[PDB]
Length: 311
Image 1 (cartoon, rainbow, N blue to C red):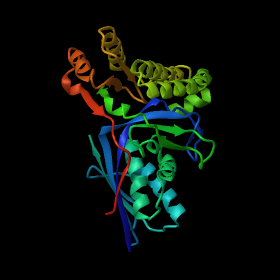
Image 2 (image 1 turned 30 degrees about the horizontal axis):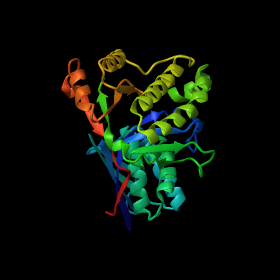
Image 3 (image 1 turned 120 degrees about the horizontal axis):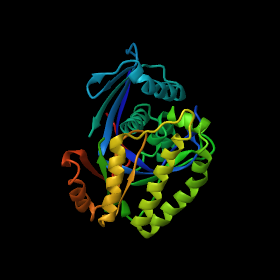
Image 4 (image 1 turned 180 degrees about the horizontal axis):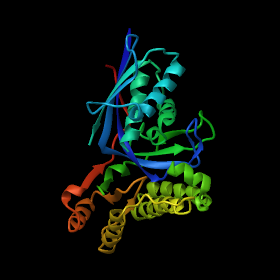
């Protein structure tokens, strides 16, 4: 009386940001977003549903998670159980291989898909993963992927963006160093954010079609900075930046001045991710190694979409 399943999902980094929910219950976003799935960072998850379990159990990198650390896993398990009419508690065993919260919820969605025999299409697996976290719905796919905001549970999902293999020519160098809801509800800058997203997405699509890296980089770098500007108009205002974040961004601008085309983006924290061409990757690493230790520069290339495994 047990059913089990496994999946592996890779992290993705949003180039055009997901920023703000239109609907909290279904995680429908205020705007569409576009990411690059990465090869170096991923999560593997096995789920077991067993009539003999007495409670839900979540183990992460060998470590039993407490109730607060298990809250999102538990809500997702309840959602997928309600849909399957499954009445069994579960054991979730996950291992991060090194953003991670979204690789992990994507992998849980895949593992539950396998265990409960849901037979989901990639589109419908993205919709399920969306209910765990917005960024998880893009990690169902490899390379460039777009989460179409839609207007409902049925129409909000992600898809791969064919790029004639341009993603295999690109890299990302990581420099290790409620806010969303507050911003939607209170920032005087949020409309300006919304009014610029579609133009940015259109230009990314045009950049991808012509393999125009400086165009891609300029658009996504401004898109990220526009997202971070909105938090300074929230009430109370705040920033995700740390002192080291600003140093990294200035150094990326110095790199561009020294002739290395590269562009930075940040998410809901202080790490800085730098988009760079592979053919220019060692040159960037050489320039940044003059200011950071090689150990603080973690590289990554394009990665695949979700992989499912029977147990």
